[PDB]
Image (cartoon, rainbow, N blue to C red; front, side):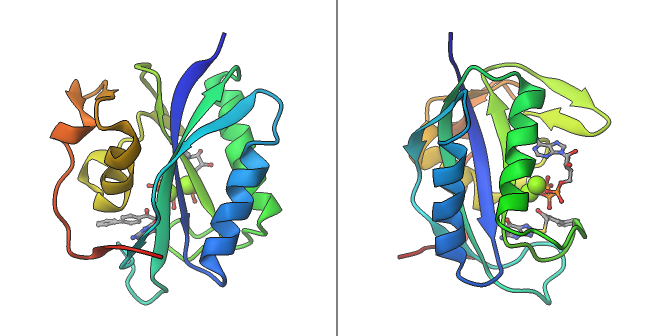
Length: 159
Ligand SMILES: Nc1ncnc2c1ncn2[C@@H]1O[C@H](COP(=O)(O)CP(=O)(O)OP(=O)(O)O)[C@@H](O)[C@H]1O
Ligand SMILES: Nc1nc2[nH]c(SCC(=O)c3ccc(-c4ccccc4)cc3)nc2c(=O)[nH]1
Ligand SMILES: [Mg+2]
Ligand SMILES: [Mg+2]
């Protein structure tokens, strides 16, 4: 039995589009993960620390038989495969893979919160997520993504 989950991907170092497309390929290669939907890519001004490069961001849907922790380990392993060496949470990275949603399940462990607890105020997440998951309910707010998404000029259609 598979569950539907959503991942947020980001890159702001180097050939960002290549790193994102390699990430999707690698995610689809883990036993127990199948990438089932892919959003458009957006180019986005960096949020937080601004003296760093512009990001490309997208979202994917996966069908997975993995538990949430097994899925997290696959996300981190993918970052390692793309040579994410920097680990300053505020700083640049070759690849970031974040778990956004895992069905309607909710957890807030010290080091793992799903739904991702910052997604609802990030246009760099909600805009691509709405492209693939408009009618999906975000279980904290209990609102559909299409009712969370908002306009943001710092998020531009890329490609
Ligand atoms: N839903 C989630 N997805 C991925 N990582 C999560 C997570 N909730 C908590 N984390 C934690 O965040 C840790 C550090 O990961 P980083 O990728 O450097 C943070 P970031 O992606 O820059 O910020 P963000 O998670 O606010 O987007 C992970 O090892 C994990 O323990
Ligand atoms: N557009 C864009 N900006 C990004 N900044 C980063 S650094 C980690 C982070 O998410 C982050 C996001 C937001 C704050 C913040 C912190 C405090 C106050 C306001 C914002 C910090 C870090 N990742 C991306 C990305 O993927 N896209
Ligand atoms: Mg992140
Ligand atoms: Mg991350």
